[PDB]
Image: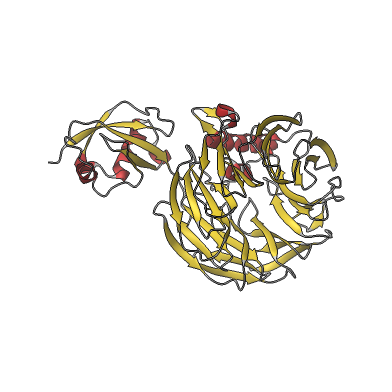
Amino acid sequence: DLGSFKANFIDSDGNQMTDVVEINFADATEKNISNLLNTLLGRDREEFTPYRFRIHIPGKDLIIDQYPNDLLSLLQKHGVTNPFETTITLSAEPQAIFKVHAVSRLAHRIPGHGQPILSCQFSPVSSSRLATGSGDNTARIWDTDSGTPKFTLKGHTGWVLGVSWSPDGKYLATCSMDTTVRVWDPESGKQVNQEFRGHAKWVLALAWQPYHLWRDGTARLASASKDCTVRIWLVNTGRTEHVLSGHKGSVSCVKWGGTDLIYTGSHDRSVRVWDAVKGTLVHNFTAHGHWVNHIALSSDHVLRTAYHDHTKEVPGTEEERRAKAKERFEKAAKIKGKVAERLVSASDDFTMYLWDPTNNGSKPVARLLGHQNKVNHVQFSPDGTLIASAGWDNSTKLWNARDGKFIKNLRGHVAPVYQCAWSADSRLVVTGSKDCTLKVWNVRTGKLAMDLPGHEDEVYAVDWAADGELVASGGKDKAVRTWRN
């Protein structure tokens, strides 16, 4: 009946995935073509990768990201005069094997904090445990199964600006205006040893060393401070291994990547890359024309949870745990077959820069222009294909993580957007706003999927648990809220 076409399958790198193959238009659904590609690649029936396909419109420079209900008509609409003897290039984008359901309603409101919540993060193990940091000088651990307080972590004498679980879930770290970092046991609620002292001013951000890189029988932890330095701590002994010095202004943000590089952004308007093992400066990016206050790595989500994944399988031994954590990172961070993390940074002049240190050094991949006010948060999607940026201009913007191109606005908030958080399958993003709402966005369609009123005041912090089940939020009204499907 309907005709056929030759298909040229290329991956995200632009490399041909299989030899050219003929496909009937009658069979040309995304599902069937995805099934076909999996088959051509020799995959096992039970190990198929779900593909979506960007269609390269023959005769022009347009790439369609949303697969059409009828391929033939899409081609004819675009003036493909001979659809039956033109090779169609299809970019294959692998999708998550699992699906995260959009949260849709309040699960629990839990009061406890006496001042605003500034930070919140789920355990990398499951959504059953949540941590928050507050201007009441405490962190808290919450039982999200029942919506009850679990532990109050007291000891800090200034605002808790950040909480961060160790990637294996065994520790929680907190940083504070009191110039200290504290490490806690989230199962017992007890502080581990003494406070980490050394910074001269407020401690602004934390980054755990990825689990698969731990050595000397200890976890390592990086802290960024207003004192313009980063310190690397040995967690077991509380000793500072390295002081990363050179920034001429406050180090507002810090990330620790899967090849043992540390990344920093500063009010001295620079973004720097450091060798964590040697404590030496590797790259100094000076493109920004204003204070840098936020950075993100393409690999953040996979490094956030070490060996913990959607399978809920935890390997038995230290070695196996390391191996699985490493394998997950390398599978997620390889571009063109080589491990290569990307970095995005934001300055107060509304600008973002996209970096590929491995392949570009200090020449940025792209400059990301479009926001009409400051960026308050930026996150790569877990699969590293997209960037979401939360703006003071009431918008969240989506960008291509490969070339920095603007893709679409997420419009809906009526006040500054303070944070965003990706679902683990890269399909959804949740945002929290000054307007006291959370909104869940369908990334593929660009549309509001779910609107979540409830908070009595501004929302400062949001997280989407890696297992997908719960979203958490907190802000000026002091009570934590969890959200469920």
Asked which colour scheme the image uses, the reply is secondary structure
Q: Dividing the picture into quarters, in which one does residue 324 lie?
A: top right
- Residue shown at 54%/67% (left/top)? 437
Q: Residue furthest top?
A: 19
- Residue shown at 51%/66% (left/top)? 414
Specify whether residue 102 is in view: no
In this image, 165 relative to 452: left or right?
right
Toward the viewer: 465 or 421? 421
| Number of numbered labels in the structure image | 0
In this image, 329 relative to 18: left or right?
right
* Residue 445 percent across, percent down from the top left: 39, 54
* Residue 241 percent across, percent down from the top left: 82, 35
* Residue 92 percent across, percent down from the top left: 38, 37
Specify whether residue 238 is in view: yes
Toward the viewer: 463 or 37? 463
Toward the viewer: 453 or 152? 453
Toward the viewer: 124 or 104? 104
Q: Dividing the picture into quarters, in which one does residue 37 lie?
A: top left
Image quarter where the N terminus lies is top left
- Residue shown at 62%/71% (left/top)? 457
* Residue 68 percent across, percent down from the top left: 28, 48
Q: Residue furthest left?
A: 1
In this image, 301 relative to 98: left or right?
right
